[PDB]
Length: 128
Length: 234
RNA sequence: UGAGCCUUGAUGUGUAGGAUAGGUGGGAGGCUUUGAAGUGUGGACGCCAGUCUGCAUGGAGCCGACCUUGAAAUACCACC
Image (tube, rainbow over all chains, first blue to last red; front, side, top):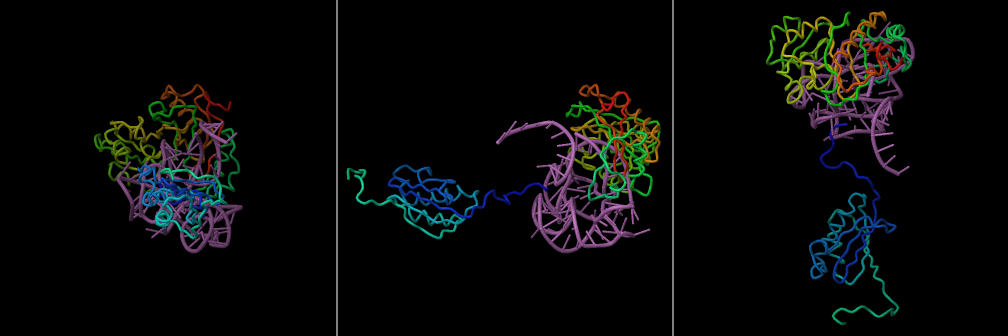
């Protein structure tokens, strides 16, 4: 043994593959990478990037949530994603564009918003 | 107690256990596990009941043994303050500090004492180095140094050894040759056991000697029972 | 399932170098079962050229000190 390297030569898992789940919400966007069985490995957000409701709800805040979430899972040795998205928010493709641009390989993008057979009475915003 | 490595293997069919003998059979055995063509210098390894990890609380000093050690009496002195020529004339082969560091690490490695003055010790270990820390060099920290270099070399040419330990229970010191009889060997051991007791630190035990062993140059070690008035194996 | 002391196997922090100077202290080219050296190559270590380690292998053979990384050395023993 020599003295150790200046930047790591090695990484403790190499599971290769996962799913980026995005909840692009009406006030925010939340990005979490999870292993293929849905146990979450790391996450990051719009709102934690110095933004309130009024700015965290934008595709630009969401774009940054994707980068902090790509960094969140770096040690689990994932690089391959597919993508799942829910919620009315605009964090749905600018997020993905910056997700892929933070060193991951996307292959599929699929919606997982639950839609009803009529269902129950909706929540109200602006008394609508 | 013999060790096997890739780097010298001739010992494996000459010794066959990590075992302790009375000294009257240990030196009989050491003559088989001798690996050089020339008759080799022999060492004790003296393991101690000392609990010190601080240099000042470890054993430190030197002594003169009644009989020879097979050592050359080429003697080296690190100095930039003390009497260089009076040291060389007292029977030292080599004197300097920038390139003595190279001179000691060539030809025959059989020094009785490589001395420093405390005038030079800065560049021997701390800011400068002259061999790297290893037993062959005068210790950067403990009293193994004197500004009376011309005395220290005249002691060294008498077949004097050097003893100290640091974080581990080890004083290694040359004690004879492998041709020795066990009384000559025991009598240099008894001379050194006086000299570790006279230069004993407060943090050493009552049962001051843990184990003693005897070891030839290219060849292996085997262990002895002897530590006389301080043996744990009694 | 947590921790130490110690013995041992692996491993060595003063950085780099072709590479692997923990300490302490001694010391140097060696066979009769085996092989290091060194080449090749798996392992380990890591800097990408190598060593450490095992095997193919030499087994009348071979690694230091010159040279070199560096403030400074480097067969190879023993101890912790």
